[PDB]
Each structure stands twice: as structure tokens, then as C-alpha cells.
Image (spheres, rainbow, N blue to C red):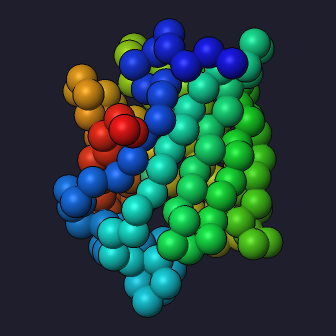
């Protein structure tokens, strides 16, 4: 396991800073009663030889998902039983994920942009953009 090498690698924790996230959640067709708000969220991204791991956790929601990815290579995961296709790529120093949710005819853009000490995550679906800011853990 390697925890450095790219600016977006590391252990990231959500902050109080969030923008337009309910509009993004609504545009995905998800209920705000269970997916809105600003619950403490962790992103951990590290390298394991020939691939990366990306662990997402939302402890209040009993959610933990470990995503295995190789840059530029498609992968799949599941949420409940919604299949999710993804492909992570680098845009220079930033990390992007292209996400298909075929059952719902949705395409989602995720971006991870590290401004130094801080990580800005941008979420886009169609013309709806949300942002959330993360800090390095501890
Ligand atoms: Cl498509
Ligand atoms: Mg997040
Ligand atoms: Zn796209």
C-alpha cells in the first residue's frame, strides 16, 4: 500500500462546506429524506501495486464501499442492487470518474481536485452541479 504519489491519494473527511448538494441528489432521483444533508463522509484512496482502492464510508448511514480501480479501465460496483459502471481517469493532477447508472439512464461526473490540504469534490449530472469540500483526516 502506497498513500502518496498523487495529490488525491490519502484519507479525506467531509467538512461543513457543501454547495447545491440537495439539487444534485434530487436530480439523481434519490429521496432527500435519506440522502440529503451533510453527513460525515470519508474518502480513502491508496495504491496497491497495479491498482488503486477507493473506500467511501458514511458511518451515520452504515455505508462502506471499497472500489477497486485501474486508471483508464472500466469497473463495476453495486449499490443495493443498482449496478454502477465507472471509469477513473487523471486530468493532469486531478482525478475524475465517469459513472453510468444504466437502470436509471443516468451519467454522473465526479471530480476530485486538491487545492492543497483540502480536496474539492464536484458532482455533476446533466446541467446540475454540486460541490463538497474535504480535509485531510486527523
Ligand atoms: Cl450510455
Ligand atoms: Mg464524498
Ligand atoms: Zn461524461
Q: Position of residue 81 (x, y in %)?
A: 79, 72
* Foreground residue among 25 and 134: 134
Q: Residue furthest front?
A: 138
> In the rendered view, does 10 fall on the left or right side of 84?
left
Query: Where 1 falls versus 58 (above or below)?
Result: above
Q: In screen coordinates, is 15 left or right of 31?
A: left
Percent of width and height locating residue 63: 63, 65
Query: Which of the image's four quarters has the N terminus?
Result: top right
- Is residue 56 visible in the rendered image? The answer is yes
Image quadrant where residue 82 sits: bottom right
The quarter of the rendered structure image containing the C terminus is top left
Q: Which residue is depicted at the point 50% across and 10% down? A: 5
Q: Look at the picture and state if 136 lies above or below 121.
A: above
* Residue name at image x 51 percent, y 72 percent: 60
Res 103 → quadrant: bottom right
Residue in front for this viewpoint, 2 or 94: 2
Above or below, 7 against 11 in this view is: above
Amino acid at each position: 500500500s502506497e498513500w502518496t504519489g498523487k495529490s488525491w491519494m490519502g484519507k479525506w473527511e467531509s467538512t461543513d462546506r457543501i454547495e447545491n448538494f440537495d439539487a444534485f441528489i434530487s436530480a439523481l432521483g434519490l429521496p432527500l429524506e435519506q440522502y440529503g444533508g451533510n453527513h460525515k463522509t470519508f474518502h480513502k484512496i491508496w495504491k496497491e501495486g497495479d491498482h488503486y482502492h477507493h473506500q467511501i464510508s458514511v458511518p451515520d448511514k452504515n455505508y462502506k464501499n471499497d472500489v477497486n480501480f485501474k486508471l483508464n479501465e472500466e469497473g463495476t460496483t453495486q449499490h443495493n442492487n443498482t449496478e454502477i459502471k465507472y471509469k477513473y481517469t487523471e486530468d493532469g493532477g486531478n482525478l475524475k470518474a465517469e459513472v453510468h447508472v444504466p437502470s436509471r439512464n443516468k451519467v454522473i461526473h465526479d471530480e476530485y481536485k486538491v487545492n492543497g490540504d483540502e480536496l474539492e469534490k464536484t458532482y455533476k449530472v446533466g446541467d446540475v452541479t454540486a460541490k463538497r469540500w474535504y480535509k485531510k483526516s486527523s
